[PDB]
Length: 224
Ligand SMILES: [Cl-]
Image (cartoon, rainbow, N blue to C red; front, side, top):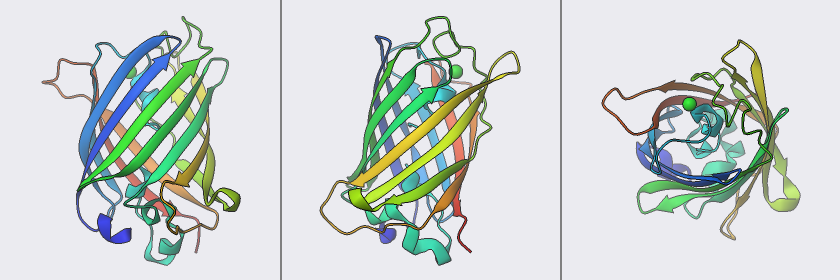
């Protein structure tokens, strides 16, 4: 699996979403360079206006592009599952608001690394921070704490994302994650460690569709 990531890899993302019955679709394209932990992607809402804030979809919208230190390469579950891939499931609990439940398959289709996602959101407040679009277009959170899930031949993670609200407050998004291989092949089950991620959000000044440009750098750490 490692060998599939030594160069620059094209990425395709497809998301189908339904949040309190507000249906939407997102497509994304770009590339990943795992040697540097570097992702460059542009996402488009193909159905018109996105009915939730873009920052709330960042974590849902390819941890196989993380840079694992040489000394930690035996802990890289995500690449080890390739090319057949993995299922990534989350529940994201927005404090004092609704929750997303996501199921994605991350796998190669030829030379392209594909992330295909279904997102279901329920129990949101129609005038809350999410459906009311009260979140700032920025990102402040960084670590994903990974542990092995031996019983499921995979991993789990939990981490908190804080999203800045327009009034200076923060909207917590508590993430619970589980990943399992798609194939029957072997995978690497890691010792406890984390991924340190930074995501920078911007706009394409020539793009009239609702969209998000993302530049991300991700490095594994915590074993030394
Ligand atoms: Cl937004």
